[PDB]
Amino acid sequence: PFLELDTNLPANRVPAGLEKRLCAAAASILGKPADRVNVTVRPGLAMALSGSTEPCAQLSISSIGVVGTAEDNRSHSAHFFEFLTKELALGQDRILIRFFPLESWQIGKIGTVMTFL
Amino acid sequence: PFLELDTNLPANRVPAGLEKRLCAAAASILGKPADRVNVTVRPGLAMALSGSTEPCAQLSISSIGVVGTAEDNRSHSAHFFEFLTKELALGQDRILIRFFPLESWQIGKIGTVMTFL
Amino acid sequence: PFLELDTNLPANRVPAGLEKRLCAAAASILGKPADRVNVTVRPGLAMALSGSTEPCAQLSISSIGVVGTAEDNRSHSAHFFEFLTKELALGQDRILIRFFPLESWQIGKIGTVMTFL
Ligand SMILES: O=C(O)c1ccc(C(=O)O)nc1
Ligand SMILES: O=C(O)c1ccc(C(=O)O)nc1
Ligand SMILES: O=C(O)c1ccc(C(=O)O)nc1
């Protein structure tokens, strides 16, 4: 899975090791191995969420097969909100998630695409 | 109900009173009175969870009738996770639960088995 | 949470399963488990809302901890209006909400009160 987390929390208000703990969390939530989880955290940004500049965070989640239905994404959302509200000390009104299905021909790995691996 | 909690948190990082609070919580969650709840806490163990020796806990829950279905246990799990995350200051990736149905002929109580009470 | 919805819509103009979908929405909005959400719908009543007998609904919401501030209730209101206007086919002017904090000693469950659970 590919996870990108944008936040207006400064780096020194994002707990040490979050990018590693999000690999374990995404592995369990999405049912793919932790060694196939990719996380990017971009702290210190200027953000408004629901019109408000109080501390907040945005997560994008991309994967083949498992983020393409409302019913699957409902379950995924519940678990990611539980994890991130606690880690970032944010209320559930201060986080939003977007889910993006991917296909194998879009993923460039070791100089080819996943279609040929 | 019968609850057994193993943790690699030392005893002095397990909050005082956890046993009676877990009796009350198990009454709320499983529906059987607090005075029928049995709790065993084993702290200071050497543990790995998901391959990692960071602080963690395992809970076993055994009961007649109420821990035997996926839909029952999904609900029970959500509540026991919320209870333990708060009490032990652990993330939900650092807790696992196992559920075990029991029958009356397996429970020895006051020198007989529950079949005869 | 405890939700009570009065409406002058006849029962056959309240969509089938509304009490179930409002349960799930209220769990999300209030940040409480769905197996702790209670919904009561009372249709076919004689009602005036804002002085008018046109189709309308009144919602009451009661919960520990999460319905006691203006800022929290503004957030909750926005989501409940978005849900109910669509489900009941009512304009924003035809719904009102009241929020009521509860305490643990007020809630009777399994023959005791939540103070002891
Ligand atoms: O090879 C990549 O790391 C990779 C490729 C695919 C997926 C995925 O579908 O989630 N995740 C990671
Ligand atoms: O008498 C015991 O304490 C007892 C016996 C049975 C059960 C139970 O099925 O949950 N719990 C407790
Ligand atoms: O455990 C009960 O069912 C319960 C307890 C509390 C609340 C509540 O605060 O809204 N709702 C339900």
Image (cartoon, coloured by chain):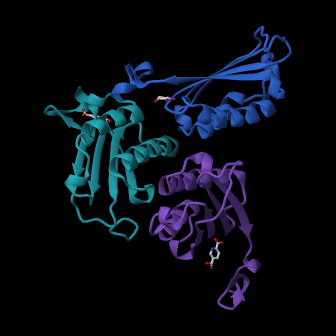
Chain colours: A purple, B cyan, C blue
Residue A4 location, x and y as percent?
A: 63, 68
Name the image quarter holding the N terminus of chain C. top right
Residue in the image at 48% along x and 65% along y = A12
- Taking depth in this image into account, of A28 and C94 the one nearest to the observer is C94
Residue B40 location, x and y as percent?
A: 23, 46
- Taking depth in this image into account, of B15 and C22 the one nearest to the observer is B15
* Residue located farthest toward the top when viewing the structure as drawn: C46
Which picture quadrant has residue C107?
top left
Residue in the image at 52% along x and 65% along y = A22
* Residue located farthest toward the right when viewing the structure as drawn: C54
Using residue B105 as the reference point, say whether residue B96 is left or right of it: right
Which picture quadrant has residue A113?
bottom right
- State whether residue B7 is above or below residue C34: below
Residue in the image at 53% along x and 33% along y = C66
Residue C71 location, x and y as percent?
A: 61, 36
Name the image quarter holding the C terminus of chain C. top left
